[PDB]
Image: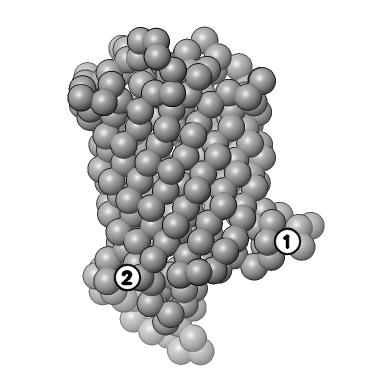
Amino acid sequence: GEELFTGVVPILVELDGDVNGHKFSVRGEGEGDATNGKLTLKFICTTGKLPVPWPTLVTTLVQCFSRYPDHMKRHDFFKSAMPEGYVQERTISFKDDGTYKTRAEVKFEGDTLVNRIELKGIDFKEDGNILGHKLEYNFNSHNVYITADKQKNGIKANFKIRHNIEDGSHQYHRSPKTLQGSVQLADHYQQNTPIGDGPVLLPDNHYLSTQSVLSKDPNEKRDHMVLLEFVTAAGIT
């Protein structure tokens, strides 16, 4: 488990998606450094233009790279499930808009940590913030609240993602939007279960403090996202 993450680990992410019938695929590659809670990935839309905003896929696109402090190592379910891995399932409910349902397997394939995801999105509004591409190219910082799911030998998580809504204040100096109008909320409901049959660590309640930086590669012609993430576990003193 945790022993597999003490160095720098290559990462592969593969996603097939269907949102309101728009099919797309994403591939990401990079590396993870759990000792420092950090990973760096570059994602490409391999099917052309991504039909949803990149930020709406960030949570779907490897919490095993979180940095658990020494006193909290006993609560790291994600690494404990390795190398066999875990299934990660979510419902993501966009306020006043559609829903994503995701099923992923996160596991080692050789020396590489691989996240393979199927995503289905339904009931999106054509001129809403998602299909209308009205989201800032960035990502707020969040607390991901984790609890043991004893019944399933796994974990559950709940959290509320705040996606910033775009304007460049077009042409004129517009007042900043009121809080409710400035964000598109995405309620996340998450369940993880081990793939292997051996013992896993079932945690006490805690959270992951996540921080993300989104950027572009100036030499990349494909629709893409470069992502840095830094995540630490907390909530137990």
The x and y percentages for residue 220 are 76, 58
Element on which disc 2 rests: loop
- In the image, residue 97 above or below residue 6: below
Element on which disc 1 rests: loop
The x and y percentages for residue 15 are 57, 48
Amino acid type assigned to the residue bearing label 2 in the image: Asp
Quadrant containing the C terminus in the rendered view:
top left
Q: Nearer the viewer, residue 172 or 81?
A: 81
- Report the residue at 73% width, 61% height from top: 222
Q: Are marks 1 and 2 in contact (CB under 8 Å)?
A: no
- Report the residue at 27% width, 34% height from top: 156
Q: Which residue is mark 1?
A: 222
**Disc 1: CA contacts within 10 A as few (<14), some (14-19) or many (>=20):** some
How much space separates mark 1 and mark 2, taking CA atoms?
28 Å
Q: Nearer the viewer, residue 85 or 31?
A: 85
Numbered disc in front, either 1 or 2: 2
Task: Name the residue at the bottom extreme.
Answer: 171
Q: Which residue is mark 2?
A: 97
The x and y percentages for residue 64 are 46, 27
Question: Looking at the rendering, which quadrant does residue 151 occupy?
Answer: top left
* Nearer-N-terminus badge (1/2): 2
Q: 11 left or right of 55? A: right
- Report the residue at 54% width, 68% height from top: 22
- Report the residue at 38% width, 77% height from top: 125
Q: How is the image coloured?
A: one colour
Amino acid type assigned to the residue bearing label 1 in the image: Arg
- In the image, residue 9 above or below residue 170: above
- In the image, residue 133 above or below residue 148: below
| Residue 162 in view (yes/no) | no
Q: 120 left or right of 187? A: right
| Residue 202 in view (yes/no) | yes
Numbered disc total: 2
